[PDB]
Image (cartoon, rainbow, N blue to C red):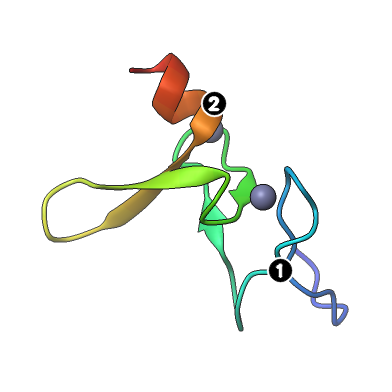
Amino acid sequence: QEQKGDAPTCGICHKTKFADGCGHNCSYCQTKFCARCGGRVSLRSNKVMWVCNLCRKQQE
Ligand SMILES: [Zn+2]
Ligand SMILES: [Zn+2]
C-alpha cells in the first residue's frame, strides 16, 4: 500500500472507481472489485465481507 494519489479502481472492468477510500474487496482473493463484480456477504452483524462473482459463484 502506497499513497500516491491513485484513485480506486475495479480489478475486473477497471472502469467503476470506488468511493473515497476503498470499494468492495473479495473476502477471499482480496481483489478490489465494484458492486457489480461481487456480492455482499456479511457474517452476522459485526463485519461486512464482499465476495467476487468468481468466488460467490464457484463457492456456491
Ligand atoms: Zn468491476
Ligand atoms: Zn474472490
Q: Which residue is located at x 47 percent, y 26 percent?
A: 55
Q: Which residue is mark 2?
A: 54
In front here: 26 or 17?
17
Identified by mark 1, the residue type is Lys
- The answer to whether 57 appears left or right of 40 in the picture is right
Up-down relation of residue 17 to residue 41 (above or below): below
The picture places residue 29, in percent across and down from the top left corner, at 57, 33
The picture places residue 35, in percent across and down from the top left corner, at 51, 56
In front here: 14 or 30?
14
Q: Which residue is located at x 61 percent, y 83 percent?
A: 20
Question: How busy is the neighbourhood of tag 1: few (under 14 within 10 Å), some, or many (20 plus)?
Answer: some
Label 2 or label 1, whichever comes before in sequence order: 1
Quarter of the figure that contains the N terminus:
bottom right
- The answer to whether 47 appears left or right of 31 in the picture is left
Q: Is mark 2 within 8 Å of ligand 2?
A: yes
Q: Which residue is mark 1?
A: 17
The picture places residue 13, in percent across and down from the top left corner, at 76, 47
Element type at marker 2? Answer: helix
